[PDB]
Structures are given as C-alpha cells and as structure tokens.
Image (tube, rainbow, N blue to C red):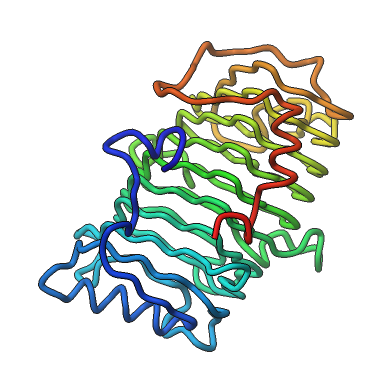
Length: 324
C-alpha cells in the first residue's frame, strides 16, 4: 500500500479483494461504476484493469465520473483503476473522484485533457483515502501559449483528505497541481503526501497549496519555468530530501515580491503559507534566500532516501510500465 497520508484513516486498498473487470473504453468504465452503484452491493471492491485507450469519443460523459449514481451526497467506495502494461491510456479525458473513498489510480497515462474539468485527475467533494501511483500526466508546455487551454494535471479540492501521490511523472504542462481551489478555509483539502514523483518542464503550481498540511519528499523537480511549491493562506509544507534542477525564474513576484523559485508565496491569496525545509538539493535553483518558517512534520512513519538517491530512483522507476 501507500506511504504517507493515504495510509492513515484506515489505509487505502482500493478495489482489492472483490471483482475484476477489464475495460478498454470509457463507456465500459462508466458502466461498470454505475452498474455497481445501482446493485445490491454497491461497495463491493472493484478493480478495473484498463487495456485500451479511453477517449472522449468512446466515453458517454466528458470525464470518467467516479461518483455514486445517487450523486455526490452518497459515497462511492473501494475501487482501483489500474493500467495494463503501457496500454492504460486516457487521451483527452480525465477522471473525477467525487465523495470517493478508498480509491487507487495506478499505472495509467492521462493527457491532453481539455474537456470536462480539463484536468487529468480531479479529487473533490470530500473524497478520502486516495492513492495516485505510477502514472504519467502531461499536456503541452508552452504549447500554443495559452496556459488555460488545458487545466490541471492533479487537482484536489473541497475537503479531499488523506491522499498520496507517488511515483508519477508530471510533464509538459502549465498549471500542474492545485490543493484547494479558492481562499475558503472551510473547503480546503488537508493531509496530502507527494513522494518520488518527477515534475519536469512545467510552468507553475507544483503544487499550489492553500491551507493544507502537505509532505513532499524524494521528488525530482526539473526545468520549472516560473515557480514550483506555492504555499498560501496558512498551508504547511514539509519539503524534505527533494532534488531540484533549474527550478524557478529567480525574478521577484509582482504580487508578493517573493523570489520565484522552488518554494515560497506567489501570485495571490491574502496571506502566506509556511514551509519546513530539510535535506533538499538545489542545482541552478534560487535558494539562498530561503528559511524554514514552520517546524511542521507529518504524523506518520515513512522511509526517506537522500535527495540524490531519490533522483536516481525517480528516473528509473517513476511512471507507467513499472508496476503492472
């Protein structure tokens, strides 16, 4: 199972120990979800192996809706969506988790998502215990120059909690990851871990964090054009043993005045978040101006490599075609 926050609150096992289905179109995936939701046993664990390319053309809605058929007031539980080999591909259509509990998304590539939420994975409406592992997410950067043509890669909103994002590649994209979509503390997610991801050729939001407590360890950040970790409105982020290469422009942000770099407070919200920095390696990345501004450490056990060991592990073992 997952390291970090998805291991808490009872853990995350997804669809393990129930039914197995193989799907190669969005119609099959959506029907499996909805048919189960309408059954006598709606929480029976379900693993869906994805062995074809899921698209707008072969899906009945503009996103893959991991949501109870009785709408977001009701929970949907105990699902894994796992790619087969390098064949689990979502081209132009993303996944949304809404009041979704104990969910694994693993070994899929999701990319060029413009329609729907315009986001590869949206985790929202009070979802909890979600593990996003060994995937690849991308669009274009700079592409056509319109940062909003695509929306997010992995966004968390509306009280999503206990989430681990591990071993993924996020590449070639403008607005990479959100944690909290608005300055409303009562809707903020909390308790997110990011580890062993590759964040490469991105403009910003790595992540944009509002309010939440977040642990980022053993990630490899590379070629990030504007800024990476943006901690806002009382967020606390423990940034531990990560490797950064060519991250941030070094220019002062026109809104907050903060030097654009691997961590800080940028662009907006009425006040800063905080960051605890330990063990990071910064190459050609502005960093001498940084101080730790919180002692925040997460409430769980974990194993952590050095930054340079992590860089090599991420190079070798992140993304698809590794675990399945």
